[PDB]
Amino acid sequence: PAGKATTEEQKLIEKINAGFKAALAAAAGVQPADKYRTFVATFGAASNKAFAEGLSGEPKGAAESSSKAALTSKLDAAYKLAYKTAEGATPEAKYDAYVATLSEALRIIAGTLEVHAVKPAAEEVKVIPAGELQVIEKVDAAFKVAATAANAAPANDKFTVFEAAFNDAIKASTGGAYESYKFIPALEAAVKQAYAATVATAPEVKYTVFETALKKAITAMSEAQKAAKPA
């Protein structure tokens, strides 16, 4: 699990620079001669060292050489292509241009070997479901003032009071937060039954159903705090 992020190529590409610098750096400061032999002959050793240090297999992937082929094919291609151009390049600056050419070719490889994942909207959890359940404490309490102050109704407006405090009390205390019965899903649908039930129901528990189901439903949701039954 996330054992390693970088790879031998990506990781090594930073080390080969030192080998190359030893050769490229040695190119200048020396006599007009011997500057050519080292640039071509020292590169052989420098590239061999990285390759000799990039020894990897990774049987997990089907690729065995293709992964390293990209590094060497492009690396040698630019090197040989960059040098080859020097032969045709204008003697006005064929050597400086030649050396500069690799650096760019060599630098871009670091940009082409980048994972390049970029996955907008990877689907992340905005909020933990375990929380926001505690607020049920107030909901259960605030429910009382809805039950009594409603009961005082003369058999009229009784619901209105609930719809008043239920929608208000929840929002009024927390106006700037969860403005609407959403803090805990299921209510939006489950509540809807209330109007589907308190219309055609036996004439005896018409209110009791409303009192019992709401309290009962909210209680079940109470057990959620104990355990959210996580995978």
Image: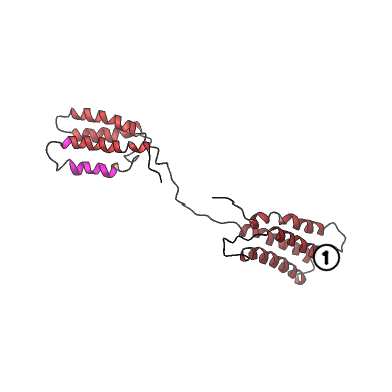
**Nearer the observer, 91 or 22:** 22
Q: Is residue 51 left or right of residue 153?
A: right
Q: Classify 223 as above or below 102.
A: above
**Nearer the observer, 218 or 161:** 218
Give the magenta-colored segment's residue range.
Answer: 188-207
Where residue 171 appears, x then y in whole percent? 32, 34
Location of residue 198 by image quarter: top left
Residue at x 65%, y 58% (from the top left corner): 9
Where residue 129 appears, x then y in whole percent? 39, 41
Where residue 172 appears, x then y in whole percent? 32, 32
Could you tell me what secondary structure mostly forms the magenta stretch?
helix
For the question of whether residue 139 can be seen, the reply is yes
Where residue 35 appears, x then y in whole percent? 84, 62
Name the residue beneath numbered marker 1: 37
Q: Is residue 159 left or right of residue 102?
A: left
Location of residue 150 by image quarter: top left
Image colouring: secondary structure
Residue at x 38%, y 39% (from the top left corner): 227
